Image 1 (tube, rainbow over the protein chains, first blue to last red):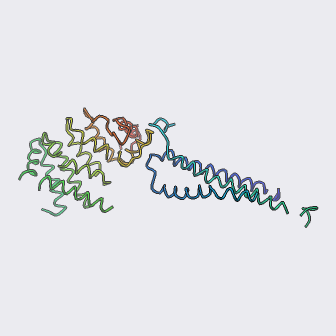
Image 2 (cartoon, one colour; image 1 turned 120 degrees about the vertical axis):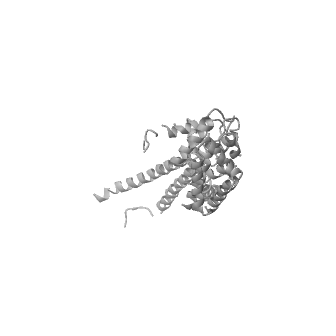
Image 3 (tube, rainbow over the protein chains, first blue to last red; image 1 turned 90 degrees about the vertical axis):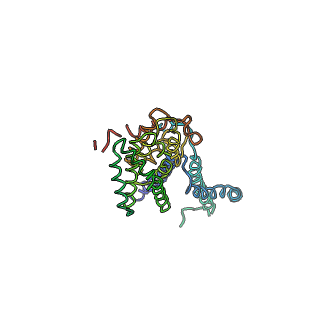
Length: 72
Length: 52
Length: 205
């Protein structure tokens, strides 16, 4: 029972992550449609500062290129 | 449907759409990194993987 | 008699005295000529500052102040303009503050509203006072939201309706709300969808 039941645990976990993505996506669209309104800012920019940082960090440059495929 | 029967436009939505892709993107990357690590592990002794 | 409580009952007693079109006129003169109306608005203005700067006793005093202004302004004539210009500006300012009171000032404002063309200052106050906080997208709902946010409680709405009933009686400015939003009177009627749609489900006949 246990050895081939790992299946349910793994399946459950992936389902969890997909539901998390949809949860987040629904959570996010409830903050664009009710929320503009065009009110939205304040706290938002701080979110937005964090997000900016992380995003092109990543980008750019540096990382990607060099590293991932000197490694591959 | 309701919002559509309104003046118009939608906005400041894109940022979120960016956030989710941004949050999503690395998830993409963790997989790739996983896809690497396994390969590295795979590169390692032959004639018998099944040994002790 | 200065004591806040005596002062507020004095205001109430006079309201009772103001009853005839004729009596109302005397009450008008009492303050104007032989406490003056100006002192009264001043008190309201002061309370307003204290309230906002801060962010029962006052409610007693203010409620009385309004009850009195309302009683006279209703039973008056050309005089209405004079009181209108003066409590109108101050009353508008008071309305911005939360206050329990909001409705009441709206009722008084309405009394002030004149029959003629010179509605305009009042319409601007109202539109500005719905429009200011709200962020309106280009849709309809956002507009409704502006009203809903401000006119939170039942008294607020009833007062609002009385004021609106008065202003709408016979006229308003062209391209109202110009600059801030899609112009025109239409969004106000939409708001009523919020109201008389809801009415069926009142509390409280």
